[PDB]
Image (cartoon, coloured by chain):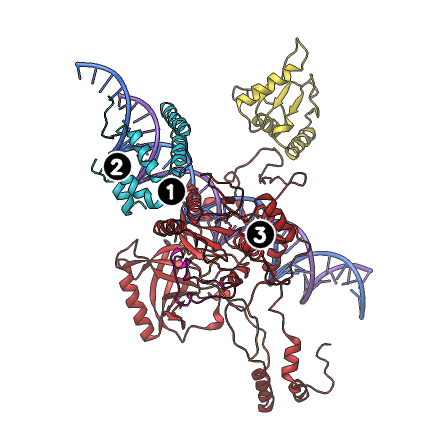
Chain colours: A red, B orange, C cyan, D yellow, E purple, F blue
Amino acid sequence: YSGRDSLIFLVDASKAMFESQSEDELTPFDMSIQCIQSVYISKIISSDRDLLAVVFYGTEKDKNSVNFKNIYVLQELDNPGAKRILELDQFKGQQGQKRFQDMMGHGSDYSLSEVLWVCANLFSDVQFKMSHKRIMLFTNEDNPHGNDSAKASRARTKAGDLRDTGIFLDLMHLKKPGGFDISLFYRDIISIAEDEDLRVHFEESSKLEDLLRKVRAKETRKRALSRLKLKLNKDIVISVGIYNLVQKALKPPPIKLYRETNEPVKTKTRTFNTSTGGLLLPSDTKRSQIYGSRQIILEKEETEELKRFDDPGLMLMGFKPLVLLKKHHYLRPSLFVYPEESLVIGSSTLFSALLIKCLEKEVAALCRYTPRRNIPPYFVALVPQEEELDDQKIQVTPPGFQLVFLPFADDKRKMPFTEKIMATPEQVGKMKAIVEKLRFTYRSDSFENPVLQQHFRNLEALALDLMEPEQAVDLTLPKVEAMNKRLGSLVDEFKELVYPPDYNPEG
Amino acid sequence: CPGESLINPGFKSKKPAGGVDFD
Amino acid sequence: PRDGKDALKLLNYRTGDFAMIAYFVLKPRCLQKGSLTIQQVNDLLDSIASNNSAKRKDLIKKSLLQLITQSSALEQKWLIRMIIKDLKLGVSQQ
Amino acid sequence: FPGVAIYLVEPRMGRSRRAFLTGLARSKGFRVLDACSSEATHVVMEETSAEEAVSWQERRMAAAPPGCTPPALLDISWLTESLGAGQPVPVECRHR
DNA sequence: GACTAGATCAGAAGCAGTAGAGCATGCATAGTTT
DNA sequence: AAACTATGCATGCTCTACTGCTTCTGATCTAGTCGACT
């Protein structure tokens, strides 16, 4: 998967789309606008390098390269930004609907062939490589052309041509007074006709709920940190790739701006002599360190050369039982090692054999690891990792090796000596009861970083000039009320059984 | 390929974080 | 599509004339009633020729696109024949 | 050494660098003119090419009295060497 | 020949991730002065 | 015995540099058309 994903939001501008079934309900047009805005915000937060477009059909005015009738391309394929969101915001309400009607109009005819032609033309203009081509149809008219059959045939032919080109088509059908029926006309235009998507739907599509669900977490495409060589010995070498399945998420780096006109500035660092005033490059100056009441002077090149031990890669040392590995010896986040057949042919077979035998014998490969040049070596353990799938066969644990760093003698710290006091069985039983009362299931994606979420919310509020920032609920805060209700009296019994009458833990 | 993220093709959709839910 | 049947038919015409192949290809893909008069067609052809003599292809493409979108299948066939300068009708110049 | 005059071009080296250089020159005994004046005899540039230097010379002459001696174009190397030695240094072709 | 337009390769820019140094802030711990 | 100051640790933010992977752009090249000549 290489390139960018392009999406086009086709929104019908027919009269039937501007009628609300109930007074306290959202019109289909407003729902489509809200979905587009949500997708825009999600793309800005997650993938800012993607391309989006917004096109309307069935209007009175037109704006397109080919100069068709009743097709107004509101926004062409361009990276998302706050300006487009603000522009779309002027159609959200009823006054926005009036503004949209005045600007473009509604109630005119249209031909789906022209719409698809305009979409294809928009796709062709983009110069960047596009991994995905996608179009979404926000409409509530299952029979766009019932009076004319030639128009339907032309639309079918254009949809087929687009499908052959490699353009995905999706139908976000909206509520209809009568009921949407895909079988009428949209069975062929839509790229994939699901078996369940054949009955008459009396409610908006379920995909709108997914679209409205804002995702405020960055998405990174698969990439290899390094492509190194595993050396069983001097003459047996295979090629492996290293990946970081877990990586800390950081706020985007701040940028320095000028106060007067918000124009970015450039920061430069320089070093000058005090007694002469001249400028010194980072080669005239030396390095120093005061040991034993004396000064030791080393050049920069020598200082860098102090760290040269061995060439980059992994060197095999032996195999160790997994029992000897310790959980509390954590030093650094682990990495993932996978075969890489491009550099060396035959690496995959040996890697698979090693993984199978390591799983069978429950052993881990001890290795010496050197990520880059002029970096001191470390001792790592490659633990086999089998392929684990979930109920729906979606892979949850890939096959390969888990690279875990092992601490040196300097990475451990001595602990103060503390006398051991053992609790009586009754206290342990009461604590067991409390623990059982406070039991819950844990998942790796059950928590979110409050700082990053609040930062994203504040940034969006500032960019869109919203009245107040949206407040993010913190799921990491203990539920004091629920815990108190569940525990009941157990806390009092434990405190009576473990603490003297006058202890005052807080004090 | 059920569960694929509509917003981001090629990435598996992630369920909303539920925090702690006692049994 | 580059590898589609229509593209192969158009490109591989045994260099049943090209006009008939184009007419068959465009019959299910074009309108049924045009709106271009003789004067507009003459102006577009004049622009195409003048731009060709000026070494410019973008405007030639624009004019051809306008002709394609504002013409039917029969009109496109006749325009192709006129451009190729091989209009055969069974009656000579005399 | 009141005989010689030294001027530093502000718009190409920065305010902080110019201030530091002027302070060092003053502490070393050199007299540096804060503002451009006809009495200036030496002009020092910083990170500049010949074209920009000659254009600056033309601009300065455009608002200078006739029958005078325009300063000589010099590089920052000359000033740094003079400050290091503690006394004015002879001018060479490289500095010019 | 010449022009124009298609398709192929290699270098530079962007980006991600790591390491080193400095700063600021806060806090804790222990030695010296009165 | 109490107050001030030297010393150290833990953590977040920022400049600066360096290495590696991916993508975009400038540069090196064959087919179609018109024209020149013989």
Comparing labels 2 and 1, the label whose residue is closer to the camera: 1
**Spot occupied by residue A271 in the image (x, y as percentages of width and height):** 58, 39
Q: Chain of mark 3?
A: A
Q: In which quadrant is the N terminus of chain A drawn?
A: bottom left
**Spot occupied by residue A179 in the image (x, y as percentages of width and height):** 49, 64
Q: Chain of mark 1?
A: C
Q: Secondary structure at mark 1?
A: loop
Residue type at the position of mark 1: Gln
Residue type at the position of mark 2: Phe
The mark found on residue C32 in the picture is: 1
Residue D1 forms part of the magenta stretch? no
Looking at the image, can residue A373 be seen? no
Comparing labels 2 and 3, the label whose residue is closer to the camera: 2
Separation (CA) of disc 2 from disc 3: 95 Å
Q: Is residue A13 left or right of residue C12?
A: right
- Residue marked by disc 3: A293
